[PDB]
Image: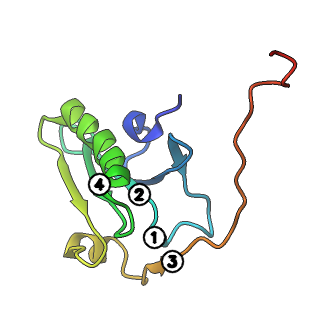
Amino acid sequence: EHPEFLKAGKEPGLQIWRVEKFDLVPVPTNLYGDFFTGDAYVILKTVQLRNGNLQYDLHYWLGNECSQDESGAAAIFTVQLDDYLNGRAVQHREVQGFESATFLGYFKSGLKYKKGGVASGFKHVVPNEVVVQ
């Protein structure tokens, strides 16, 4: 499909992404800054080291209301990125209620925690019209 987190790498700084729709989904403005407990967020940091090999680090965050199934899919994509960057990157997955200074240090503005997505805005794309039978 369109894996941006795994294919991420076009700017030395920080990129935030979120899993949604059985694929990778970015977090538009206004939305960024709020972590969800019913989903997984994948973040990849990129900097320019002396040699200029562009350092690549990534943190895998999961929600407490996401059994190993949802957390498994998120960790799965994170594990692949590692094999691709099993050179010396910084891979570290964080959980809700157990974050670390790295996270609290990456965002000190005060990350908001949203819970319960009261919204039935979601439809399944059907295969063209039912003309076929």
The mark that comes first in sequence, 1 or 2, is 1
x, y (%) of residue 35? 45, 70
Please say if the residues under marks 2 and 3 sit with CB atoms less than 8 Å apart.
no
Q: Which residue is mark 2?
A: 41
Q: Earlier in the sequence, mark 1 or mark 3?
A: 1
Q: Residues within 10 Å of mark 2 (few under 14, many from 20)?
A: many
Q: Is residue 5 left or right of residue 128?
A: left
Sequence-wise first label, 4 or 2: 2
Q: Closer to the N terminus: mark 2 or mark 3?
A: 2
Mark 1 = which residue? 35
Decide: marks 1, 2 in contact (CB < 8 A)?
Answer: yes
Q: CA distance from mark 1 to mark 4?
A: 18 Å
Q: Residue at x 23, y 30 (%)?
A: 84
Q: Amino acid at mark 1?
A: Phe
List x then y, in percent, for residue 87.
Answer: 12, 35
Q: Which mark is residue 114?
A: 3
Tell me how far mark 1 sits from mark 2, CA to CA. 8 Å
- The kind of residue tagged 2 is Tyr
Quarter of the view holding residue 131: top right
Q: Of the residues tagged 4 and 3, which is closer to the observer?
A: 4
The quadrant of the rendering that contains the C terminus is top right
Residue under the point 34% across and 50% down: 69
CB under 8 Å between discs 1 and 3: yes
131 relative position to 54: left or right: right
Q: Secondary structure at mark 3?
A: strand
